[PDB]
Length: 541
Ligand SMILES: O=C(O)/C=C/c1ccc(NC(=O)C2(NC(=O)c3ccc4c(C5CCCCC5)c5n(c4c3)CC(=O)Nc3ccccc3-5)CCCC2)cc1
Image (tube, rainbow, N blue to C red; front, side, top):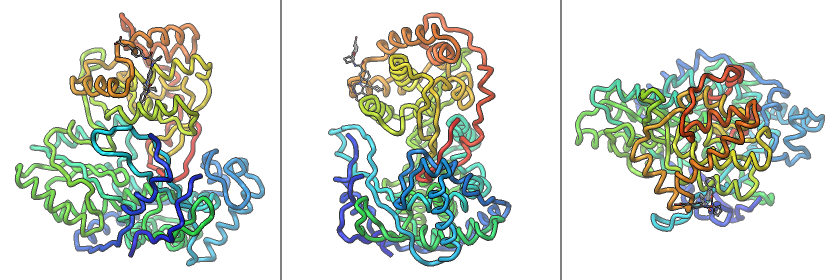
């Protein structure tokens, strides 16, 4: 079947990516899928199902599901918004209960979805190509989204880890991800690793893939209504349905993965894992270790030789193609762990204050800096700079540029204590910047404040990026951080801790740094459990 069918009605509005480029994306994501399954696929599936069998999932109440709704989640077309949902307003609640009742009674009628072009900031690079088309987002109404949580929130939070174990990427903090990859690399006699990039993964997801995914969810111990709701949501929403633009016009139909449903991340991880594990067997890759985050796949295995490794990747690719997961860029074997870019990141190493080696995750800073520049220029709902400070806290660029720039703005605006929204693995977190030292200590360890001896390649990538973007050099940032640090120190409490810990790299004579006592009190239990991209998930912490 066709991933999409279109009426010709435009994807209407609600460098930055806009609805103008939607037509270019539509051409790429629109194709017929030809999927051929074999015994390797069937074997891996049965193994996954046996692990899913151990899961017991709870049905969330309306109230618990309402509490997970982001405050700025798109309003319902039925006369209520995200604020009404969170406040448990009679109208919102009554509508949610009728949506739920309808899921239990109607097992066939397709549910309507809205299609929108996503507005994302990318860097204006005229040397290696041109502007990227806007990504497309497909999501059901707010009432349906609350119902999805009731039936599947506990499933999507618990099941992926039970099924995939250590291969489930979203259970890891950046430090644990680094440790997993380093351990996997070290465990091989002669390691070889590769990233597998699927061309438009969401469009490659077939109706059968979605039913196979349900077959895995159905192995859980579930309440009868949860079981019916999962069955109904699969047929009416997950497998496909009609697409409506922002103007309420019929845009066409979808027969592939919707990017804005609760099961997107979980389903994509399960599907990518299933296909990859089966393709590993077809390719005869030896002693495979996989790390899967949605459509992002990394494989670490035993090298069989240079030519043999090239042949085994072509074989893996041919198998993924048969399973309807063809490649964007063909995979390349790597013989150094640092050379693998997975989840847009690479492993790097630094030294702590005692000279001990510390592995950390980094990435090219172009996109994070350009997005930070967009956010500094215009008020945004999500602060990517805050997410990048949290996730890339040990990096040279996040410490010297992002922390220095944003802490000077927060000092000037006197908004250090004001909670900000940021995204962590697709979920929305409301965070006070004053809590950053505690968060960083918990996710990366005390050493994240004392790291030095950065690699020449990492130093050069940062410095070249600053030049290209017209950002002042690192020496200017050191000078700026000293003033930012001094002002934070003068304020006391958490503000002084931000100065002392985040800006210890800036001082002539570096301070001792003892663990932050209150850091253990932060409840980070919901943090690196699961991925919720497009899942409409929220938490205050
Ligand atoms: O001695 C030497 O060798 C050179 C010294 C030197 C060179 C340049 C400056 N720049 C400045 O003073 C100003 N900009 C900045 O002090 C500045 C700060 C952050 C900037 C950012 C980001 C960095 C990440 C957080 C958000 C802001 C960008 N750009 C920035 C410029 C350059 C810019 O203007 N825009 C972009 C565009 C894309 C990406 C980054 C940038 C402020 C007044 C006039 C311009 C200062 C000192």
